[PDB]
Image (cartoon, rainbow over all chains, first blue to last red; front, top):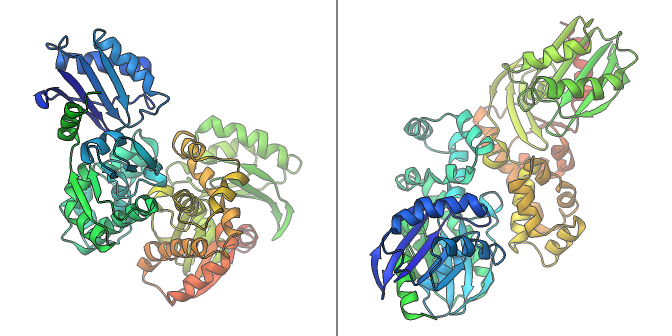
Length: 283
Length: 283
């Protein structure tokens, strides 16, 4: 059987599959070769990953890991860490999460794959490998339509009275926050992006309000403009992955349609897709 | 004679005046009671400030300091540090930079005072003290029209091909930067706001380009909307202070006019204003 891992800027989703069928589905966190180092991740592997699989650990004949930060320079580091987890594993491949998304959504055909979660991302897929990628630039310089960006845009306007009366107080009280706490978490606390992206549920639950809807709409439009248009392939349908793409699917459809583009598909997780992929693309 | 200090999120401007006349004009940096602490600023005072005045240090009968971070809670800390600088000083007052701006621009009359520099700020002045203030929220959540925000907006669109062909390469080469260096400085380097606000000269020098001009224009408009309109006093003329307000004065005028508001005045520094103020408002 095989071990498939999909790591994002929040948690890591694992699955032990056998011939296109799932036998295991764990839930760990973090794991990023560019953000973390050798042993600070060597601990998560054998304290979160191993104990989760622990049983058919010897049945793992191959492992495929997909995660943000798995640059072609720091990927061989997680490969070593994983290889020490299952030293008797035959094949261990580490690749970026963008590629994992394209393989899950596109399969083996040409197309554009996009991620809409804590952060945003996009790539032109030719069917086997990524041909072009627009660097997301992060929640401060880019990541359009991402949950971290929706979050900072939202609380910004909310705090400055651009939302209906009471919404601000309704927001602050639900999360027991104040303006000063928000500043502290955003500017003097670690992972400000995750902090900001954690208010998506409030936004999604308030799409019935104009100011909120247009805010989400403009951000998604912005994402297409600065991340998809530039590929110059409006013939290719847009495939999306991620919590935000899913939770805001309706809005995402309207935006795409409004620009004359066609939606290929939107799914929260690429897991089901990666299972069938490594079931039909052994090597 | 008196000592006047105006500290911003970059440097601190000093001036030794006597009866509305300047006798000294020093140039130090930093100095912020909320961002820094007791001795980490107790060193700048007697290594940058004292050696600059050093001479008429005994002629200083009073000192008036204005700086961002001089909250009514941490102000009494810089007051103690300053008081140790000139232990024989009769009067030592520490106040926020927003108040210093209003006193310099408004003098002793009612009005709206705004700061447009590294960061943005605004307040409703009643002629003697601030009546209302919209928290700027910083370069990530707010600071509309500020140089840090203009900077992140600009490099973001630039990096994502939203500017004319060649501008990106022209920008990166002038500053010897690459996309990866920008990410590193913005997300893993101290004072990302100052880094971002240091590209204003490039922007100002390219206002002849549409994409650039509308970018600056929309940000200034945004600043008015979320920072000035809410005061509900379009009868009061807008007074501005700061490097960005000055360098972009033309654009700032058009924006203000376009919203039916009237420009009161725009000056780079409030120094000249603070000199006359503490010359006509002894106590």
